[PDB]
View 1: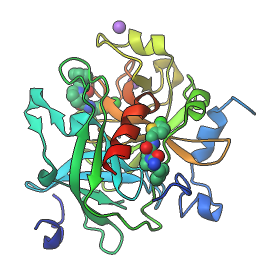
View 2 (view 1 turned 120 degrees about the vertical axis):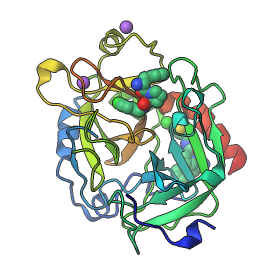
View 3 (view 1 turned 90 degrees about the vertical axis):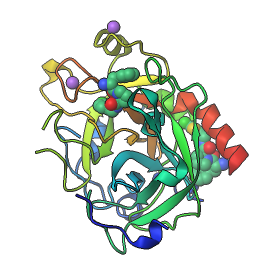
Length: 11
Length: 33
Length: 253
Ligand SMILES: N[C@H](Cc1ccccc1)C(=O)N1CCC[C@H]1C(=O)NCc1ccc(Cl)s1
Ligand SMILES: N[C@H](Cc1ccccc1)C(=O)N1CCC[C@H]1C(=O)NCc1ccc(Cl)s1
Ligand code: NA
Ligand code: NA
């Protein structure tokens, strides 16, 4: 339900 | 840090604009008026 | 938030979303209190009855948001956690006494029109304003109703009066402590509104009429249902926990 966030924040 | 300006909103207090319901809070505050 | 309304842009620039990394979902609200520190409820991070025990790497904070679900490019900022601190006497076993936690960010956040910290109240500001009938303001992205209109498109806001302590006590069988206060309208008052699931950890704020600054007096903590007649929302009493907040920040900042 949430828009994906940039990958840099999940590294 | 944020200390000097804490609690002063850029889009409201900083520019002397009020939000649509903050007056409801003020009206409930009896002490000191 | 039940029976609230859409926030204005920049109305609550200290509002923080606690965001679970995997699966990607809202965990809780929170508030920005400096460039590096975020305040929330302990039960947002630790609640063993529900098998909840989050570590720093499980979570992100999202600051500057308005939309619940959208990635607000060029507006919101996303920060990683360096360390969580939970009050050592947080009572998750019984009644959520001392329901408070701090999170230190890995890097300072840049303030903007949408990102700005709230003040925490001194003894005198707390004593003047934490009085029955005086209204504060609660914000969050939690449920719009107790059961399910389900979840909001944007941040919601409701203004609610502080309730007399005997009325709070008489509304529930849970043991209430001096580290809590309650707020909401009475059945005879007509108006409605409450926090709900998902609003946990967000701020109850008041605008001081003495210096025209916003102060965080409470943290959304617990309730029995949402917006039920004769029930009230309960909030962690921030000032009562000042010594612990100051000790953590003085020692680890
Ligand atoms: N309905 C229970 C009531 C409860 C249970 C154990 C200790 C204290 C209070 C409750 O409230 N619990 C259980 C733990 C977490 C907390 C919660 O959901 N908090 C969010 C809010 C909903 C409506 C509000 Cl108003 S605050
Ligand atoms: N030494 C710093 C200074 C500071 C920095 C940014 C914003 C406000 C103040 C500080 O003081 N900081 C950091 C944020 C939080 C606040 C603090 O510990 N305050 C404890 C309490 C006072 C009244 C309460 Cl109620 S809790
Ligand atoms: Na009771
Ligand atoms: Na109620």
